[PDB]
Length: 247
Ligand code: NA
Image (tube, rainbow, N blue to C red; front, top):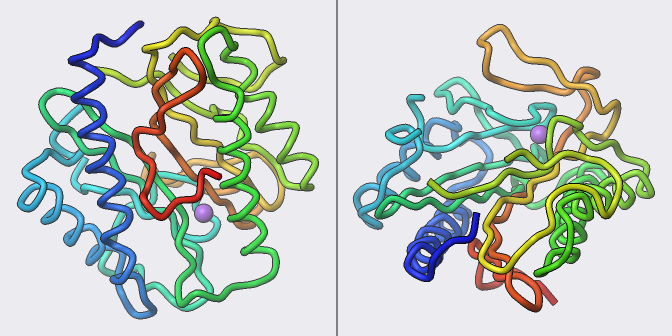
């Protein structure tokens, strides 16, 4: 599962392009915008400016997932989903370039202001991802990631969605368990770390469209995602954004 130098170089490019989607879409996020409009802007950027491939061509009909509020993941862009101030929005994107892909998602607070709880949920979700990323280096264990995430999130009185906290990435599902469990990590491995944090119960449900996932209790959910490369001394965050403080 060790990526070659050529494979890693192509993943750096794709990861940077994916990061660029999440940064460039920011000024378009305001009250009154539909999530379909965001999808079209991202599709045009990926295909026609980056000259890359959005996920709807690789292995449905949209270039991004737009998950609002109680939607946990896989929200479908829609002309009828109109953002309003105080909404929390996750945009999830995969960019494919030259056979390799970069995967990342982040939260946006529509209008810059939201409730005490929604702000805290987003910040805890981002810090949870970072805590999981902080365990990773050559010789660490896959289980260290989920353990760090779950311990932190529950200490903050939120719930972790139990389906997964990450996946192998290339072209393996990361679960919550005990530290020291799972595969020992080696420099050159790549995967995503993407914990989903619910304000209420950890249970989710799939909507009638067999695609959109929502919290079981209709409370808020937040997620962040990075694609990471394992190194001898730590990680390289392939989807890091330039103004993103990784300390
Ligand atoms: Na959500």
